[PDB]
Image (cartoon, rainbow, N blue to C red):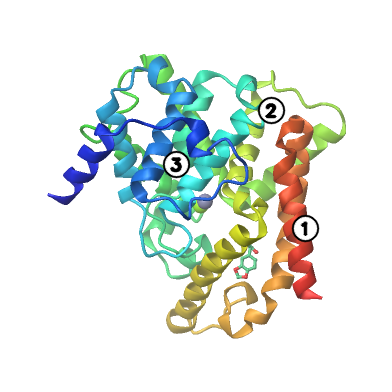
Amino acid sequence: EEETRELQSLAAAVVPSAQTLKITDFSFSDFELSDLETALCTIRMFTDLNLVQNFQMKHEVLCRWILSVKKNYRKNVAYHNWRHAFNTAQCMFAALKAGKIQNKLTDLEILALLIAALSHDLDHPGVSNQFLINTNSELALMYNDESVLEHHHFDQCLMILNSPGNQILSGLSIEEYKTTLKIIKQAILATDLALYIKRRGEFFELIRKNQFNLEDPHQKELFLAMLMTACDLSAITKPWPIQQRIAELVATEFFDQGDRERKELNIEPTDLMNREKKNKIPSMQVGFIDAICLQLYEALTHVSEDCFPLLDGCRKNRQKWQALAE
Ligand SMILES: CN1CC(=O)N2[C@H](c3ccc4c(c3)OCO4)c3[nH]c4ccccc4c3C[C@@H]2C1=O
Ligand SMILES: [Mg+2]
Ligand SMILES: [Zn+2]
């Protein structure tokens, strides 16, 4: 059996230190890592956030859950595959550690954020919410056209958490378990960019008006949503060669969707999904950075100055894309 060898290899491995694995670095790249090494990095994230000890996760179970999460990404989807989920979780770990966010959060919040980061795009089909709506997908019907994909990712997350041998939350008390699942749902839903756009104004205004207070539960929840977005988008902050390579993957995925829209919907794709108009990429990247990314990384730096490297990297990529666009 093939998946058994994977598990036995993972569970038998000594997990290298976070220092060795370079996972505290906001500039981290996964490109040179094997799948087994990404799994070992994930075990280290749970370990160094004190989650294994605290919640008494059995090693074999954590290993199985990680491998189940990885298997439930679609490997041939160009961008939304396990490496994107892994990178998102690594950004979350770096923000908590290097970015000094950890001590602002509870143990349950940290547990939920890590699980959510890893699970937030599970079973992604490589097409957008709008595409699912337009092709009358049953998922869109079930979820009333609202955060369609994200509902599905959450459903998948729960399925894996409940699967025999994978129950990494089986040790929590009833009140802790309830609380954790609620946070996970909110965290995964927050990764719908439409929800980020809807809610970010309140976050930015709280900050601007000197009203931001993490002791307020509603504001804590809002902050967690923003932090999820920040991690989900973090490829846009990476050193140029890394960001360029990842941007090519996203383009491949999006252009694939446009091809499907021409065939299935008989419509010209929007520029973002139109390979015929790939000349628009630089200008679209600048526009995305300016409209969606910069304000978020600026706000995050306001919350914790040690998150500044995300903003610095974002600004550097803006400059590089704009040099291409102009
Ligand atoms: C909805 N939406 C809008 C959008 O404009 N983008 C960007 C982008 C910009 C220009 C592009 C592009 C993606 O693909 C084709 O040309 C963009 N740039 C990245 C760099 C790295 C990783 C993901 C992205 C995305 C993802 C992101 C997105 O999800
Ligand atoms: Mg998503
Ligand atoms: Zn994502």
Callout 2–callout 1 Cβ contact below 8 Å = no
Crowding at mark 2 (Cα within 10 Å: few <14, some 14-19, many 20+): some
Q: Residue at position x 57%, y 74% from top?
A: 273
Query: Within the displayed image, which quadrant is ligand 1 positioned in?
Result: bottom right
Name the side, left or right, on which 59 lies relative to 104. Answer: left
Q: Amino acid at mark 3?
A: Leu
**Given the image, on which type of amino acid does mark 2 rest?**
Gln
Q: Residues within 10 Å of mark 3 (few under 14, many from 20)?
A: many
Residue marked by disc 2: 219
Q: Which residue is mark 1?
A: 290
Under circle 3, the secondary element is helix
For the residue pair 267 and 24, the one nearer the viewer reads as 24
Dividing the picture into quadrants, the one containing residue 95 is: top right
The nearer-to-camera label among 2 and 3 is: 3
Residue topped by disc 3: 118
Task: Residue at 60% x, 29% y: name it.
Answer: 97
Local SS, label 1? helix
